Length: 9
Length: 24
Image 1 (tube, each protein chain N blue to C red):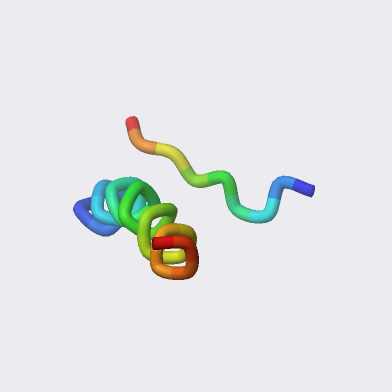
Image 2 (cartoon, rainbow over the protein chains, first blue to last red):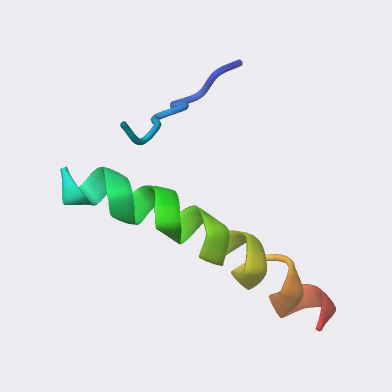
């Protein structure tokens, strides 16, 4: 499950 | 947000601090 796939921008 | 930048950088370090710290 996608836990917290935060990403840059 | 600097926090997001730091988190994304910290991941690269964690992979070397949780793996090599138990294999090196």
